[PDB]
Length: 306
Length: 304
Image (cartoon, rainbow over all chains, first blue to last red; front, side, top):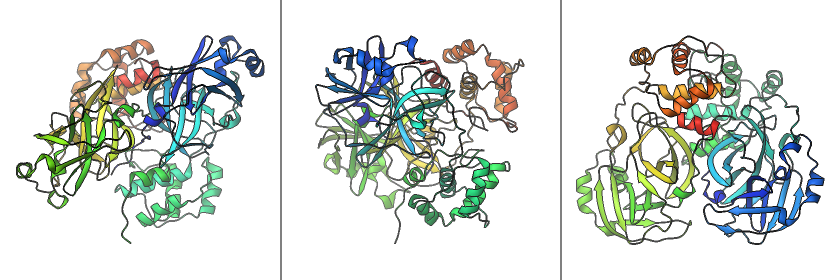
């Protein structure tokens, strides 16, 4: 029992992290097979970060402009033998294939989805934490200068989905990055100018998951027979900066396990949003929305008599 | 910027995890050098877990009673060539040294100290999270049956300090385990009977660190010129379910960086304990005490 924020074991991703340098600038990259991925802003002199001309920067490079180091973990000696730009990322080709390349995909994640982040500096894995892709296409992380190129991922069995490469900080504790197709989440630009940030929202389906976790952990004071339909809830959500609730198999499994209907927790959310009545839920006195239905199912896993 | 619950990368410890089987029971173990550490209740069949006779069980075992297997991972079989009971742990000697043994030490953590946990089932790592040793010598984690033998540790410079091997659940969301000398944190018994826990307390020094983190993340609304002395705070703490505040260099570095004295934050704590009254600190409406001064200094100033 218990529900806490937890991340995937990081070892197989740690074996893929490298340091990438372009002249005077250094950041992190991800080595898979004969490719190293990194932020294209490694090419940009400090004094040009407010208005980079990335096409001109790329033209100015040769394969010799870049180096890749891996001194940490299983060491490797790598030479850059090709370079290309794909959106907001560089795709470097190296002469040695990573001998510990995991089975992987590159698939962009949607808001409300959680992933593990391996925060790195100078190619050294430093910490790991879990974030949720927010409704405004930011993540709420902990990153300092030099963390660009840190990666985010999920795992399903042995298959890793690489979904995030860190780029920038927008505001205190507010971050964003690229998907591995080279697009930036939220269409933010890798340019240091002001950029519009849409308002964040509570992720309704995750709040529902957390309340189910609470019930499964013997905290059910907020359950009443009162229901709010998914339709009425969604109408309310549009007025109260909650996301649209979309039910899933994962949420349905929690409803079956607890015997409490989704609609009972939608009603509970509307009430708890106005106040917790001097009470706590799983040690919190405010709504929690970064525990997904999948995370709760994994943490409260049980055999089922049939 | 930002402050989040964070754990160490787990790969070095992943490379040390094995499963240990004895009879019908399979748990996790930690393989370092020619030694495998695991919970002693691996000996006790599941139906006997509420009143184990560990001495009688131990007398009945031979080296052949224990099977140790390492999963891919780098593969390894492994033969047990010795065994000893050390408090609530078994220390098994095996015939092959772990070729990926990290630089390590064994430590015993104190209340308020944080460590990373690598949660494992049948020798396979499934997740990692960070906990604090509570003032009542429990931890608040997320563990299911089969997780015993999971490993808690910190990393100091180049060295892993192993400090916890998971043993049991005491109540919902409330766990304990042992140090590697075999001593259970909080002196709880490794048996499946109800055991009373001491009342938990807020970890004062960690609440201070978190308030400093808040100030360093543009959240300083609670700062006033008012002060409460360390001595006066600690008298108040005895009566109000707070631990004794003891200053450290890590805390002083935060005081210097922010220009806000420890005593301003001790006063703030005394007012905030009564409730936040519709206000938030770093996204929370309650006091947070599982961010240590060292964690804050790392996350905010990068001070390895």
